Image: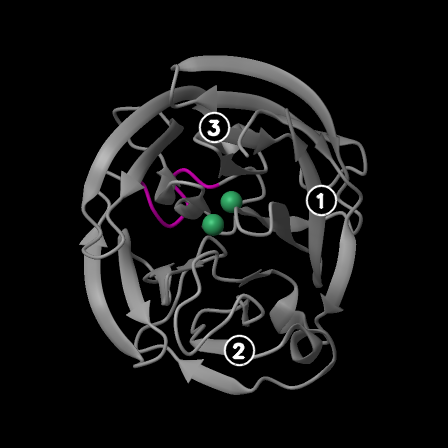
Amino acid sequence: GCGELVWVGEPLTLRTAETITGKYGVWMRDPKPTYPYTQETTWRIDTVGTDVRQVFEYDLISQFMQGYPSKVHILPRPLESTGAVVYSGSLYFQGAESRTVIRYELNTETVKAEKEIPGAGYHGQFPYSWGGYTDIDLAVDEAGLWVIYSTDEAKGAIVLSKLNPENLELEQTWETNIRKQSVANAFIICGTLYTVSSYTSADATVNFAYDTGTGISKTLTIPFKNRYKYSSMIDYNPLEKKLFAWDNLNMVTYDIRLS
Ligand SMILES: [Ca+2]
Ligand code: NA
């Protein structure tokens, strides 16, 4: 079940990009897989450049780890940065040079919804500390779909909103006290937002928490290792109960333990 994060394991490298295009990126699985996909289906996006549109899809974990894609989707619009997620059959991603989140149904290659995140900074206003236009970070946890961002009104502090996954309407919004550009990335577990302290250090920590259920903010000191010294993407998968990350060409995963 659910609980507070109390431990992160060592990063395990599952695949390594072979070109500069994959220096940063996002890779993910669907915590609520829908036909024709399964819990093994993996998606990979190498996100260096200004016209990122190729989504690599693998039917099997074995193919993701050793082979070519089983299918490539070409997005109808270029994608921004590393914050995207897959949820219940759709890729949720941010349009380049925009504050728009797009719901792209993977099995039909159809855009089903688009939504400006109200007031969200974009394109280098409130990125995480490494930059990379990481202003807007989607997240899936045990309760469904979220987006992590900030606004002028929040003065750059992390804001997070629960999202309706069908039409992308904002359902509830919380404002933390954590300056988004002062942390390396963030993710949500069991309704609690966690941040990572550094994207370069082998001795980083999960250093802040904000619990949306209680409104309480905490400091933490849970060790977190950036094995390759440049983590551009850190998300949580609530089906696997693992962190998925992209660290300097390497697609890695971390075990976790909850209280
Ligand atoms: Ca994240
Ligand atoms: Na994300």
What amino acid type is highlighted by mark number 3? Thr
What amino acid type is highlighted by mark number 2? Phe
- For marks 2 and 3, give the CA distance: 30 Å
Disc 1 designates what residue?
A: 255
For the residues carrying marks 2 and 3, which lies nearer the camera in this image? 3
Q: Position of residue 36 (x, y in %)?
A: 42, 79
**Residue 151 within the segment the image draws in magenta:** no
In this view, 4 is above or below 169:
above
Closer to the camera, 166 or 204?
166
Q: In percent of the image, x 37 and y 60: which residue is there?
A: 93
Snapshot quadrant of residue 162 = top left
Q: Which residues are magenta?
A: 121-127
Q: How many marks?
A: 3
Snapshot quadrant of residue 195 = top right
What amino acid type is highlighted by mark number 1? Asp
Closer to the camera, 66 or 256?
256
Disc 2 designates what residue?
A: 56
Screen quadrant of the C terminus = top right
Q: Position of residue 100 (x, y in %)?
A: 26, 55
Secondary-structure class at tag 2: strand
Residue 95: mark: none
Residue 192: mark: 3
In this view, 152 is above or below 17:
above
In this view, 161 is above or below 109:
above
Which comes before the other along the chain, label 2 or label 1? 2
**Few, some or many residues within 10 Å of mark 1 (<14, 14–19, 20+):** some
Task: Please tell me whether the stretch drawn in magenta is mainly helix, strand or loop.
Answer: loop
Screen quadrant of the N terminus = top right
Which comes before the other along the chain, label 2 or label 3? 2
- For marks 2 and 1, give the CA distance: 24 Å
Please indicate whether residue 234 sits to the left or right of residue 98 in the image. Answer: right
